Amino acid sequence: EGLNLVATALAVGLGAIGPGVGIGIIVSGAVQAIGRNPEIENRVVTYMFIGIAFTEALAIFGLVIAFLIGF
Amino acid sequence: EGLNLVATALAVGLGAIGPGVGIGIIVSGAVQAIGRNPEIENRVVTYMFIGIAFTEALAIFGLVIAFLIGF
Amino acid sequence: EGLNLVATALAVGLGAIGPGVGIGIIVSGAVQAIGRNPEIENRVVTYMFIGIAFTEALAIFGLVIAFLIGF
Amino acid sequence: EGLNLVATALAVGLGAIGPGVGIGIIVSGAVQAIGRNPEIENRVVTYMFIGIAFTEALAIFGLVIAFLIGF
Amino acid sequence: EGLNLVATALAVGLGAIGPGVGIGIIVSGAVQAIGRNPEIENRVVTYMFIGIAFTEALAIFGLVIAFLIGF
Amino acid sequence: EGLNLVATALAVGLGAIGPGVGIGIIVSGAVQAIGRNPEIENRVVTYMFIGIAFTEALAIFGLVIAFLIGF
Amino acid sequence: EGLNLVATALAVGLGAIGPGVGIGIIVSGAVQAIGRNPEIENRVVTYMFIGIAFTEALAIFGLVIAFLIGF
Amino acid sequence: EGLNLVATALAVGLGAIGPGVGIGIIVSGAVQAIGRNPEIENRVVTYMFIGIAFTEALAIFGLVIAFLIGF
Amino acid sequence: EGLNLVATALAVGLGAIGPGVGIGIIVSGAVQAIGRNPEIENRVVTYMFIGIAFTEALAIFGLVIAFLIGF
Amino acid sequence: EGLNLVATALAVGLGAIGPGVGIGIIVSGAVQAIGRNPEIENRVVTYMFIGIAFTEALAIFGLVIAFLIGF
Amino acid sequence: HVEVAAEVIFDGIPGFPITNSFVVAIIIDIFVIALAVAATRNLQMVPRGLQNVMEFILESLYNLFRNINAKYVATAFPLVATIFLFVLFGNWFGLLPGVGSIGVCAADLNFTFAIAVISFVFIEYWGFRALGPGYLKKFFNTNGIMSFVGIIEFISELVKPFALAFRLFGNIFAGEVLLVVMAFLVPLLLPLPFYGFEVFVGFIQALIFALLTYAFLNIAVT
Amino acid sequence: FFLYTGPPHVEVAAEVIFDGIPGFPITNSFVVAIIIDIFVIALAVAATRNLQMVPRGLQNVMEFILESLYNLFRNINAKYVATAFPLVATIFLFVLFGNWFGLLPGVGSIGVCCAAQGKKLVPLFRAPAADLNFTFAIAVISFVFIEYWGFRALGPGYLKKFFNTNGIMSFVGIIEFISELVKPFALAFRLFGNIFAGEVLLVVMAFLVPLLLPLPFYGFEVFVGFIQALIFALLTYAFLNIAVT
Amino acid sequence: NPTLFIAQLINFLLLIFILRALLYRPVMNLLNERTRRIEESVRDAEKVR
Amino acid sequence: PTLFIAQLINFLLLIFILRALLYRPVMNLLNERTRRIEESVRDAEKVR
């Protein structure tokens, strides 16, 4: 009917707006803290990646729901 | 009818957008705190987890409601 | 007329949107405060839990609407 | 029809996001102030409760309609 | 039909996110200022309540039209 | 036909928000500047009121257009 | 039908919140700028009104177009 | 029919939403920076002109899209 | 009934929303940095322009997709 | 009908918004860290590059699914 | 079962036989007069409670207004005092004080509009009295390029009292609706202290209305 | 520059099957996975070489990569830096291999019988990263390894991390356990969406104007695939450390 | 489907085990040996002094 | 089909771009790693 296409579009758009500013401020805070001290930069670089991964997982859930709707 | 598919799209998207920026703010503030003083990472990281879990609780509430509407 | 499904989807997602970033900002402030004043946990984490309790309580009221759709 | 339930869902969703992020900002400002100095905590907590009460008033404004539509 | 009901839901629900974040930010700034300078506690409180008077006025602009459209 | 009612609800729904976030942010800067420099006064306040007026003009336009279409 | 009224509602509502808060950001930035240094107040005066004029030029595009919809 | 009217309303509103907060942040950053120190006034003014040009580019893109849909 | 009209309008508006809010924060940060120290100069100019071109690409997508529907 | 075209418009716009706003905070944090400890120039180059790479990863997810709806 | 209803009436038209808003106002006035009688005749040099209300309410508000605007708080002291010791008292009487709109065989729009009309008359009388042409200042003057919205600012000020009346009627009416909803489902307030939250919200709304009147007066000053 | 022709059409699918099903059910993903494993084994054999501390020689590159991965794992934690290092190194250069070979000439057209008929021309490439089964298996294995490591290190700790996290009133458990459980599914879906999305892009975007449009797209896709492989490798260790911590 | 997933998991596990035994064990051993040789050489320089 | 030709052309262009983009930096890094190993060997010889 075409409303499934609307559902997929809405799902991916939501899953894209969600983590955009998220990962943005993530890496912003990461580079900030690195500039404050390049000594503990490795530890914070390790710690920010799980935060990136959770947001990416939410985005992936949004995308795979659209794919599931497609099939 | 396609109302179920748009329902799942709305559920997952509107429940995932919040926790995305949420995780963003969480790990952002965590990384500024750790770079500022990582001697207390032991607790800062623990707080991040408890907070990460709290926002992921809402994330999985949205996801499980989307799954339930999908089945 | 299956508007109940989209109704509960929108309710859960768009009630969970806010408390997500609310948890994010409260724990950003708290991790900053701990990176300033660690031993104050006994009071600051109490205020943390109070603010947390309000947030997921509001989200849980949204979830009660989601279950009212079940009713 | 189910449009009344959609109305309730939209009302609670839009009435829960607002105070949901509100109280988060409230407690965020309060906790940065505390971490800055835990000597004015009495006044800080009083103003925080005032803000929490205003946000709760907004939440009730967006929430009572959910039951009113049921009537 | 129920389109007037969902219109009431739109009227009351919308115009809540912005005033909610405003209620957040007003006291966030106020407590930051008062912790930064407690000698201005009276003036900061007055400049907080003026912002209250405006943002709650916007919230009630939403609420009054919600009741007008409701009846 | 209630579509006009929906249009009015949506109109005022976003109409009374512009200042909401605006008075939220404007007061923050004002009180922070006052705390930074309490000597400067009445100039920040004149700019404060000018900004408040310019922000709330949009809300007034939204409300008056809503009234015009509602009557 | 009332779709013209929906068009007016969208025109007045959307495109107003953006400039509505942009004005607040402008004036707050100017306020802390002068608070930190009042000797640059003349340049701040020159910059304020031009920024406000441009954001209001976006807002008036939003408004006059709605008047055109009204005819 | 009316679909073009609401289409134009949505176009202008969603083309004004972005550049509004855009120019707001533009001017806030510019006034703050020039308040930090004079002698870079010409350079910050040039960057200000670049910013307003880039925001008003998208503004006029939305405006001319709506204008062309008008015919 | 003219679905392509609203499709083009929505595409243009929701493509053009992003770059303004991006470029605002973008040049605000760089101009604050250069106000702190003019040494980086062109080096920061180069860091800024490519970042702005990245969102210009999304603006191009928003315009082009509407153009395809428009012709 | 053009509901699929509306789906493509929604997908592209609402998938462009997220990365578009995010990269702004990304490169703003980058230039801030340039202005404060530019010793990390290589590190910030790498980290901002990977952060954006995630952002247009989300963007290209949105664009490719939008094409699929258009396919 | 929800049974809430709107008590909208016409102030210009004669009072209705029921007159719920008028009855509530009369009850609030009677309670205030009783408190004043108890605190006036039985008044000592250092009274506790009887003079405590005066010291902690009237003197505190006068000090706050003087801090906000000294030498103008004195001029409009009656207006702020009238805003105080009222509205909040009417809401306290209307906060389910043994009736709750039950057993019948501020929320009024007309009253709020009249209060805002009094506020705007306070503007037209006192504000810009020290200047006369102050209302015309920064409004389409020679510098009207930077003050084009100045007349729009005046209109907002004209709309500011209307919004104040709306905020007086709003929230206060909301509290009534929330209490009615709690009675219909989950009675005895709610799991949270609904009644206490409503009372605090009404008190905060009255204080905010008084402060808004004082701030509007100060803005009219400059 | 112009792209006068070449835009024949666009076609995508969830996955692709392969031959050999009679003796044992084989999908094209299994063929791709076997090829990636064979290439990895060949690289290790060449990397080993004489193994007499030979500098450079194309083995120093593999040695440096392994050393960097070991340093990253050590920085993440040290309780299981040695025992679990082979586990993370298994994902490293294997997810990377899956991301690679997607830009090979006709990667999406490999094994097509032929646009004339396409009767049984199943593309026998089916990039191992671009298959839900492989990602699901990898995530399940990683979650099982993390759970076993937590049980072995602190068996009471794994249970007390949720059940006894806060016995009085509420507790971090349940929500924490639910989040960890979603973490395996989240990791699986991450690999499912990644690589598959890159292939869909390389098909659709290059279907129109296949000249300098697919080039930056493939560069970004390769960078994203390497980033995703590194992210999964680091996230396994991060989850293990969080369980230990 | 599920059988194919199980087969892929088994193949990946076998390849990973073979690699850990042969390359990862030996590559790590070689790198550690080189580093330890350098460190013990610094110790031998100390002994030389 | 022609999709294979397009993919081959894109892969060739990508390889040509990458071989000049940072292949020299990669070679420099590899040479540096080999130099570090050789320096360790030389240091061992010297100390012994």
Image: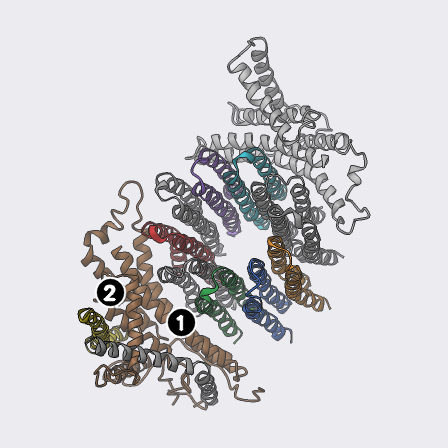
Chain colours: B red, D purple, E cyan, H orange, I blue, J green, L brown, M yellow
**Total numbered labels placed on residues in the image:** 2
Residue at numbered disc 2: L81
Along the horizontal axis of the image, is D35 left or right of L39?
A: right
Please identify the quarter of the rendering in which residue I52 is found.
Answer: bottom right
Image x and y of residue E21, in percent: 54, 47
Q: Residues within 10 Å of mark 2 (few under 14, many from 20)?
A: some
Please identify the quarter of the rendering in which residue H71 is found.
Answer: bottom right
Residue at numbered disc 1: L194
N-terminal of the two: label 1 or label 2? 2
Q: Residues within 10 Å of mark 1 (few under 14, many from 20)?
A: many
Subunit bearing disc 1 = L
Between E70 and L45, the one nearer to me in the picture: L45
The structure residue drawn at horizontal position 56% and vertical position 87%, both measured from the top left corner, is L3
- Relative to L197, does residue B21 appear above or below in the rendering? above
> The residue under label 2 is which amino acid type?
Val
Image x and y of residue B26, in percent: 42, 53
Image x and y of residue L121, in percent: 38, 87
- Relative to I49, does residue L39 appear above or below in the rendering? below
Residue L236 can be seen, yes or no? yes
- Relative to L244, does residue L20 appear above or below in the rendering? below
Please identify the quarter of the rendering in which residue I28 is found.
Answer: bottom right
Between L134 and D28, the one nearer to me in the picture: D28
Subunit bearing disc 2 = L
Image x and y of residue B3, in percent: 48, 60
> The residue under label 1 is which amino acid type?
Asn
Between E61 and L85, the one nearer to me in the picture: L85
**Distance between mark 1 and mark 2 Cα atoms:** 27 Å
Residue B7 can be seen, yes or no? no
Q: Circle 1 — which element? A: helix
Along the horizontal axis of the image, is L180 left or right of E31?
A: left
Q: Quadrant of the C terminus of chain E?
A: top right
